[PDB]
Image 1 (cartoon, each protein chain N blue to C red):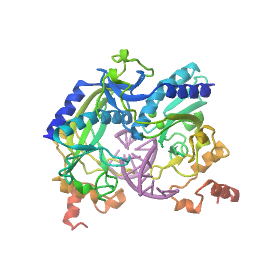
Image 2: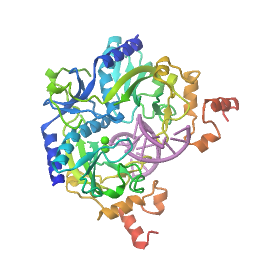
Image 3: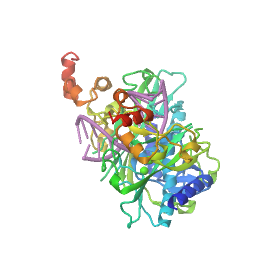
Image 4: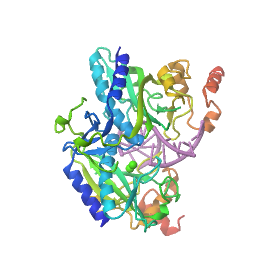
Length: 233
Length: 236
DNA sequence: AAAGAATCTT
DNA sequence: AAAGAATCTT
Ligand SMILES: [Ca+2]
Ligand SMILES: [Ca+2]
C-alpha cells in the first residue's frame, strides 16, 4: 500500500536521521533555529525525497506547486488514474497539540481556487504531521555530531485531513480549519469529531468567519448537528 | 562602524558561500527548495553567525525573540546603553530576470509600544533591514562527497543593509496581514536609499495613520501626496 | 492596487 | 478559544 509504505518510510527516516544544519557547496555549515517557521521548512525538505521514492515505487507521479499560494505540497497520481489523485500536505507544530489544516475559504468552497488541480480530481487528502518539543557560529563537516540540535523529540504521523479535523478554526484572519486539540496518539488513531468526510466538508464549507456571525448559526459540531436537524436554519 | 562592518561582512559571506542543502548529523544531505519560504529561512540562518560575529566585535549583545510573532529577528545593544537598541530584520524577495519587500506590520509595535516586539519600540534607535534578492532558478539525497552535485535553488543572490524608513513606500505590502510596502524599485535604489519619505518621522506617521482598506483611507489618504494634503487639512 | 491566499499568541 | 499577530498572486 502506498500509504502503508509512505508512513513506514517517513517513520523510519525520522528515526534514523537528525537534521542539524544547512551546508554550503564549499562545505561550511550553519546551525538551525528553534522557530517552527524554520523547522517546518526543514521537515518538508526532509520529507520530499522519501515521498518521491515511495510514490515512484508505486508508479505514482509526484507534482509540487508551480506557483506559491497553491495547495497541496505534493500531488500524487497515476496517469491511468488522473481523477483519483491524492493530496499530501506537510504540517508542523510543537510542544496536547493542534494543527492548522489549511483554509476553508479557497479550494473547499471553490473547486479551482488556490489548488494545483481541481478539488474534483483528489480522492484522498493526507497530512504528514510533525510535532517537535522545542529546546550562533558555524561548523566544519568534521563537527556534524557536535552541532546542537534545535529540537528534542520529533514525531511524525500520516492521517486523512477530515479524520483529524476539529470544529474550531485554526486561525482567524487567515481562516484555517483547525484540527482536534489532542495528544499525538489521537492523531495516529484518527480520533476526530466528524462522522464522515462529507460532514467534515459540509461543516467547514458553511462555517462563518467570526463568532459574531456563527453565533446565529453554529460554532461547534453539536450546534452544527442541531442546525442540520432543523433544516440548515 | 558596526553598520559598515556588518554590511561588509554580509557581502563577503554571500560572495564566498553557496548554501545548497540541509545536513543530518549522520552526514546525509537533503537538497533545498527554490521557494522563498524555504530561502527566507535559509538566508536568515546564513546571516545569524555573521551578525553575531560583528556585533561581538563592537560590544553588542545580540538577542533573538523568545516568542514567534515578535519583531525583530535580532536586537543588538551594549549593556551600558540599553535605551539605544538596534533592530535588525531579515527580508527576502526574488527576481525572475524592479523588486519590492514587505516591511513589517503597520498595526503592531508602530502603533503600540509593546505589541509584538521583543523590547518596547521606544528603546530602539535604529531599525535595519538586511534584504536578500535571489533570482529564481532535486528529488534525491546526497552524501558529503556529492556537494558539488547538489542543485543550487537560485540563479544568483544579492544582499543589502538599509534603514527600514529609507526604503519604505506608501502602498501596503500585504492586505489582510497589514504589512508596510517598500518602494517598488531596482536593487540599486535600495542600496542608494532612494525612498519616498522626507524623514523617518514622516515614515512613522504615515504608517501609524494608514487605514487598512480602500474605503476607509479613500476618505483620508491612499498615497504620500494625499497624506501630505491630510496633514495640511489638520490631520482631518 | 487592493484584497486575500499560502502557524502561533493572548 | 477568539482575534489578530508573524511573502506571495492576482
Ligand atoms: Ca511545499
Ligand atoms: Ca505545508
